[PDB]
Image 1 (cartoon, chains in turn orange, cyan):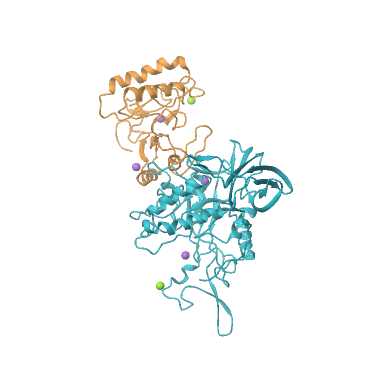
Image 2 (tube, rainbow over the protein chains, first blue to last red):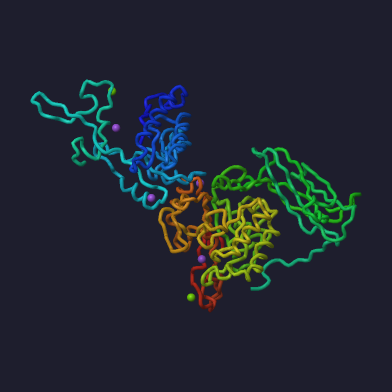
Length: 204
Length: 409
Ligand SMILES: [Mg+2]
Ligand SMILES: [Mg+2]
Ligand code: NA
Ligand code: NA
Ligand code: NA
Ligand code: NA
């Protein structure tokens, strides 16, 4: 269960989430989630949101949940996937063997990530195997690693269903439309279709 | 068998230096050090006795301390009246490493206060700090990468008698081939070896003479408390002999003797006596309570070899097992037997990628072949069985990167 907090387009990503004047607004998106969903047994992990970097407001709300509901781990990917606001190392698109040593927020080989000096936490990728178009090459590499490594406990594929919409041509025949096809600008074209199934649930 | 090392006669004064321990501790950035030397005596205790510990850098004396005997109060019965601890301040000390083996000379003078030198002992001092922090092995605050080899004391002509020429030839060759460490497999070495490593620059793993490999099971003796006295002396008398050598950075409790309660007692003993050096030991799973470092033998890079009770996990997998934190340096890897060393690069790609994979010790240095002579009087390299010896494990004595005569494989 993930809070409705995503500030991806900010520069830098944590500008709002580190700002204390945005703590009340953020808290209401975490606290009202827990108050609504906390009796559902299917909910096993809380998420503070997605792609909002890592700010002080995250740590505050992290602790709030741990104080209110000790029954569930709290995870959050932003700010390097292993901050003080996450019980689980939850990288997005961290490769199996290959390090992607980005400045400040590197994506380590998941196998390497676990055994970093001092690291003890479990690892579950909040996003992996971007299923965009003809994709999912090297999926077997992940599941080999998952089974061999106890503390590699799987991940969540990105993602389930293509985000294509229906448009009609002059004859009234339906076709799958993406970014741009509504005169929408700027747009990011087909990048909305990353599903394992088409929009009508036909398998890729 | 036989008298295979040096024999000597030492004259000591009645009132003598019976032991001396040298230690170096450092401020956060290693720009300041306190050299602490504990000196012990035998004979008549008198008020006129002193110890002077002076510290030399070539010809320049950088520090000196003089105190009478009688250590601090230890317990309710007092202290050691036959001991003294000298503490010398050393500014911006030249550090020791296999990279730059900077050495100081510490002279320990037992003398009358009025200036009668009774006797003097001495050693080379290497200002360096070894500690394991946050799962990493550190020398002077920096994570080591052990480019090591296992070395047996072997000569094709002389057997197990070591000589200076040979010892130097080994160290020249090792350092010429980018080795920075050596494992004393599997016993305390010739005294001159430690001196050479001090001077040329090699991190030494000093290992007790305890190997019970052919027991069934392997820890039958080492779990036996009746075998503790014999084992302890192999550990204690090692530490007492070599603890002053800067080149020695890690102690080892022996090799292939399983894991027994005697390994635990002794591990603790070294931790209590010598806080300066990590204690390692491979037996009984290579990650037991008897070792500060995960030190498997022949664990593969990616492949698990999951034997019951004592599995050899993929070194990458091993580090991140539930609850595990310690550094991994294989006490033995890459068996260099005959045409071997295939898959070596796989190790070094892993060592580098993974911080807590800090290297290993190749098995091993020299082929243990012996010279034999034929009907024409021509020399040839011989192995297991060639001396009528039986049972024998044939050519398994030859697993070196160099031949018996030190010619490279
Ligand atoms: Mg655009
Ligand atoms: Mg045989
Ligand atoms: Na798993
Ligand atoms: Na998308
Ligand atoms: Na390393
Ligand atoms: Na061998």
